Amino acid sequence: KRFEVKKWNAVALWAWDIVVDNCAICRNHIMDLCIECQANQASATSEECTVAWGVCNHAFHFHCISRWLKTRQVCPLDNREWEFQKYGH
Amino acid sequence: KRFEVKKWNAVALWAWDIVVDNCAICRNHIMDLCIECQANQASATSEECTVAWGVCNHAFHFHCISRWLKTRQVCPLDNREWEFQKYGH
Amino acid sequence: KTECGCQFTSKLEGMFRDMSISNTTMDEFRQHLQATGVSLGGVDLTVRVLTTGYWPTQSATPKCNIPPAPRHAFEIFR
Amino acid sequence: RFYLAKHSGRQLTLQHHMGSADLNATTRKHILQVSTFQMTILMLFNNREKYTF
Ligand SMILES: [Zn+2]
Ligand SMILES: [Zn+2]
Ligand SMILES: [Zn+2]
Ligand SMILES: [Zn+2]
Ligand SMILES: [Zn+2]
Ligand SMILES: [Zn+2]
Image (cartoon, rainbow over all chains, first blue to last red; front, side):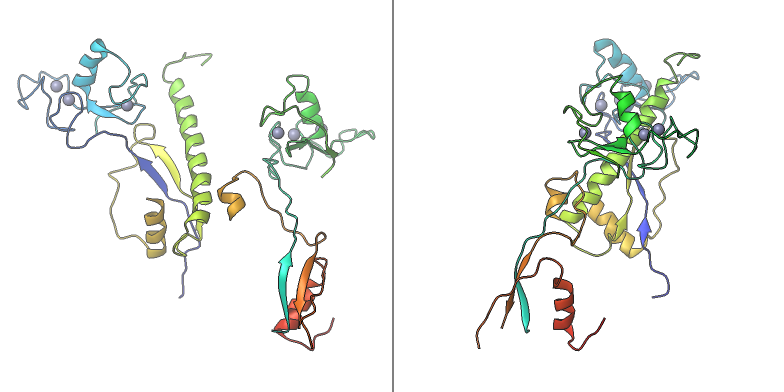
């Protein structure tokens, strides 16, 4: 051949049990509102209700894990203190 | 064939994390002076500044590990008492 | 740390821990190519493993056709 | 491969100035001996004889 690849340096990202089909706290979907929102509108009044990203690469609706930070703290799908390394998908 | 090898008895030497590209104490190179020498000359005045070899097969600039022996004792990349099994590369 | 505090600065220490994770996983996978290496598509590979929220969203992760020796390398890594 | 798979951490540098070997030659089959120095030259002779310096 005329051009042959010798080296490569991809960077491979990884995700924990974010469950893109079901938030593990309320069980609705990674997106598509939560149990404490249901209707898209439901008097949105600014604020938000997107997705929260932890340091342990787990994902839930911002609302669900914010209200779960009262029941406990260590992210439910492991035993590491839940962090907020992101906001939104 | 006319000559066929039956037995072999190579002896295989091995090296730990000597990092031939970077002394692990000062981070410059296995050779090429240290942080406490920089310039090749810098008033060499006899003395030395070669590569010290431990029993745990780790290597650093003789000076870096002699100065690290004033901070700790067990070789940095393990928990075995650092020895001086060699002097020079 | 000796200025803003231990807030958005501890986020950089987390990113450096991520760098450590990536280099370690890379060397481990080069070692396991020795055990595997079924195809010769993994001649020289340098894969890095990072975390989603840890790094700024690179993009929407494009899915365009990839080169085959890289195809075999990515298949072995996966 | 074994030393990098099981005991990952060391680097098996290659050398020639140490060891020995038993070269099985072949009227009987007399086994010779090479101390890691004549192996390469004898192998090149096996591949093709009539060589020089
Ligand atoms: Zn939820
Ligand atoms: Zn909500
Ligand atoms: Zn988690
Ligand atoms: Zn040094
Ligand atoms: Zn020095
Ligand atoms: Zn050591």
